[PDB]
Image: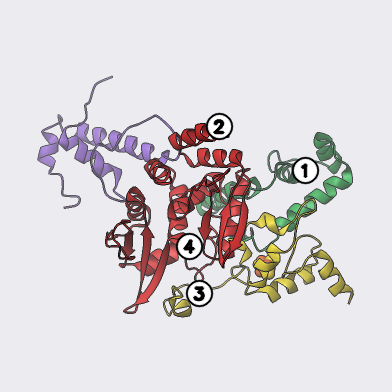
Amino acid sequence: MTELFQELLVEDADEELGWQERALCAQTDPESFFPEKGGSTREAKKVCLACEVRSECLEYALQNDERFGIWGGLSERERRRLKKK
Amino acid sequence: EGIINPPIDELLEATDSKYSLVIYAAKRARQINAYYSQLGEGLLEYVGPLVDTHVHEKPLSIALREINAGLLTSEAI
Amino acid sequence: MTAAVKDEISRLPVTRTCCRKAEVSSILRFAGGLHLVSGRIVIEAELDTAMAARRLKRDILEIFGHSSELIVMAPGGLRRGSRFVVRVVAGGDQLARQTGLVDGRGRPIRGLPPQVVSGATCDAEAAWRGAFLAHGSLTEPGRSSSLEVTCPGPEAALALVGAARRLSIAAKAREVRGVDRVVVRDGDAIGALLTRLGAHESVLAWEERRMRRE
Amino acid sequence: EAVVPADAVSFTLLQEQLHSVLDTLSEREAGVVSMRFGLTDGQPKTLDEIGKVYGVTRERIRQIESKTMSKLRHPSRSQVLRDYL
Ligand code: SF4
């Protein structure tokens, strides 16, 4: 349908700062990614599943070692066990 | 069309001289610009424009158009 | 049922520029699309309301500086529902790139533009208003209105839920039969939400109807 | 050492844009961040000073600040502030 022939051939920016700009969650409620009280961690996991820079997000999160929120489709203890493994 | 319009003679027919017309048009243009700038706020201050304008028209041109049309008055304080 | 509601919303005056931009982006994303034909991109937005199409065309012309056609021929073909379609062909690529549908010289953005999100509460409620104008319904089949508005893909629906949360108004995303929407069930949230969008007479009528029936 | 108007206007725009990003955060989060960094007054107060207003513990002030930094340091609210850095 309205796919623009996979981004088409009309582009003038020819400039990218980094993989932040390709983040899908930026098009989405930030609050849902930090479940307070008990919360849930599956809808935002589904959102991350379709992210095109999931690997980069996971790598950056692990390298900087944030212990809050859900990054790369994984929550805190998945990151912790991956770090410990 | 442009800086040429409206004709200067028609404007001068509505005032005393060029020197007063300059101040008159400039004051009206400042009023219009001030109205536009604070349009985001819900405010009752300044009024206009009183004519049909374009997407992005210089307030001075609108002021001159209203002056020519005869929709303004000048007093001495 | 909803015709009066959408008429009242369309007739609401708007002043702030950012909220107008957000409303235009929302309506274009929900009830709009792009087509690459003859080597150029053309934007087509289909509305089923009288004043809404004119409002969208005026907003485009004013803030984004573009011209539209406002054809009345029904794409459905019935010609009874007055399926208005507003078209933008001249500078379609510029409008698409500068309104948030496409960014980064890449694929169309599934969710709402990032500019609309992380904005003031006024822009969030304007985006919700545009979403309701584009698509939605007010059923009141049984005990609750089910103020449901459908969205393309989970991303737009959950973004609308997030925007509603910033208004301190409860909302719930749902998916059924492969199509997903956002709904709010309890009457209090329905009334507060409809009040915030700007409708007044419809809000009253709904209030008395609910209080008398319930 | 001459005030360049472009730089001054850029700093003013940065100052005005910073507050908006804090606005979307919860009341307590924005308040504690502002008091800790003294954006409103310019005096960075101690953790006990911040906790005195809300009555929460020192450790609570330590944690609440960390969650805000995690939220802002996310691929969901960074774009608005990436350019100014
Ligand atoms: S993987 Fe990272 S960048 Fe992608 S949507 Fe999830 S949190 Fe955002």
Q: Which residue is mark 2?
A: C211
Q: Does dot 2 land on a helix, a strand or a loop?
A: helix
**Residue marked by disc 4:** C100
Determine which quarter of the picture holds residue C42: bottom left
* Ligand 1 image-quadrant field: bottom right
- How far apart marks 3 and 1 lie (CA) works out to 44 Å
The shade of chain D is green
Residue behind label 2 places its C-beta within 8 angstroms of ligand 1: no
Discs 1, 4: same chain: no
**Frontmost residue, C195 versus D10:** C195
Local SS, label 1:
loop
Q: Colour of chain C?
A: red
SS of the residue under disc 3:
loop
Q: Choose the circle earlier in sequence order: 2 or 4.
A: 4
Q: Chain of mark 4?
A: C
Amino acid on which the number 4 mark rests in the picture: Gly
Picture quadrant of residue C4: top left
Mark 2 touches mark 4? (CB < 8 Å)? no
- The hue in which chain A appears in the rendered picture of the protein: yellow
Say whether marks 3 and 2 touch (CB < 8 Å).
no
Which mark's residue is nearer the viewer, 1 or 4?
A: 4
Q: Say above or below: C55 vs A68.
A: above
Residue D67 placed where, x, y %?
77, 54
Query: Residue visible at 67% across and 68% down?
Result: A46
User: Gap in Å between the C-alphas at discs 1 and 4?
Assistant: 39 Å
Callout 1–callout 4 Cβ contact below 8 Å: no
Q: Which residue is mark 1?
A: D44
